[PDB]
Structures are given as structure tokens and as C-alpha cells.
Length: 208
Ligand SMILES: O=C(c1cc(Cc2n[nH]c(=O)c3ccccc23)ccc1F)N1CCN(C(=O)C2CC2)CC1
Ligand SMILES: [Zn+2]
Image 1 (cartoon, protein in one colour):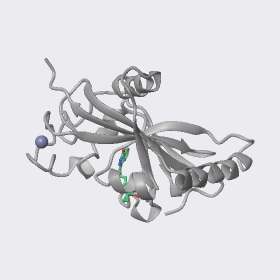
Image 2 (cartoon, rainbow, N blue to C red):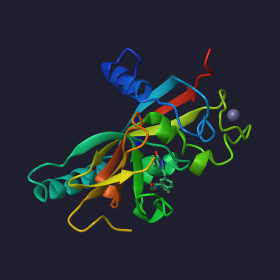
Image 3 (cartoon, rainbow, N blue to C red):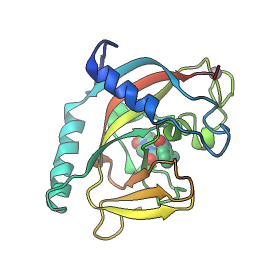
């Protein structure tokens, strides 16, 4: 029961989502190996994801977490990249298909840096790149990210040197401590704690 509403570039909601994509690009320590070499995106489309059952599932869990956390859902808007974005928007996030080999445990991963999420769009470490050209830095093929509403509740703070949530915590904050320009990553252990609100289609742009 998911429908996708296409947003006009003139819509303020399009502009604020775009800004959140563009302004959270950073350089990656892999020199572009996983996600490609770029400083910005060409945003081709932004669609709002609408699915009543998934939304009600989201807001129900949110109220639970809120009540376990001095009335604070600790809701963020975070990026998620994956080859299975088309399954996430119809069926929601599935915690049995989590990142099993994740740095912060088996669970569903999100990023503050759009470019970190961009690294997973074609697979872990970027897989083998785009399906057409096998190119992790393809400037031609269309990529997709989700910009998602995520309940973190009480988040366990894990500093990093870059399954189930810790007892009495609702999520994990994975916070880089060596790269001072790297923003955080987050892990949730329940699919109902994220709702995939926006589906963003884009290309990476070749630096001039
Ligand atoms: O959380 C993951 C996952 C995440 C990753 C890593 C990851 N993926 N995407 C990111 O944006 C990201 C950001 C920071 C750190 C890690 C990531 C790898 C494999 C995975 F299966 N999911 C994969 C796809 N999921 C699904 O429900 C779809 C139906 C199969 C659930 C969520
Ligand atoms: Zn390509």
C-alpha cells in the first residue's frame, strides 16, 4: 500500500531535502573507492513515500520509546543507502536483513553524511559498482538514497576509531573519533523505529 508523490523542485520541502543531501557530503578516507569521487550531486527526483500501515507502525513504536525516555523519541532525519530500497519502501525496514557484519552490531544502519550512505547504494563497500558499467564512481547511472525519519530513543554512545540493542538503550550512536569531519552513524534493532519518508534519485557529479 505504498504510493510515491513526486515533489516539485519549486516545493520548499524539495529544497530542504536537497540541501540536506548536498551539505552533508564529505571526503572519504577510501579516496572514493566505495562510493565514487564527487563533491556534490545532481538531484533528479525527490518523492515522498506514503504508506499508512508503515507510518502507523512507526508512530506506535515512537510513542513506546518516548515513554521509556523522559518523553523524548529522539527522532532524527537520516540517510540510508541499499540495493534493496525498492523493497524497503513497500515492506518497510526488515531487521532480519540487517547489516550482520556491522561495526556496531547486527542492525539497521543510518548515516548523517549522505556520502557515507552513498557508499552502500550498490552494495557493501560499493559492491561491484553500477549494474550497467560495474563502476563504483559511475557518473551516468541513477542512484537512490532514502532520507528517513528514525527514532533513536536513548542511544548508546559508541566512539569509533574511524541482534539486540544494549540493555536499557533503543539504538546505538556510532560516533567517529579520529576523523573530525565525519558525522555520526546510527543503528536501530527494530524496523518499526524508522520510516522511509523520501526517495531521492540522483547522480554523483564529476568534479570540474
Ligand atoms: O541495515 C541494513 C544494512 C545496512 C548496511 C550498511 C549501511 N547501509 N546503508 C547506509 O546508509 C549505511 C550508513 C552507515 C553505515 C552503514 C550503512 C549493510 C547491509 C544491510 F543489510 N539493512 C539492509 C536492507 N533492509 C531491508 O529491509 C531490505 C529488505 C532488505 C534492512 C536494513
Ligand atoms: Zn553506470
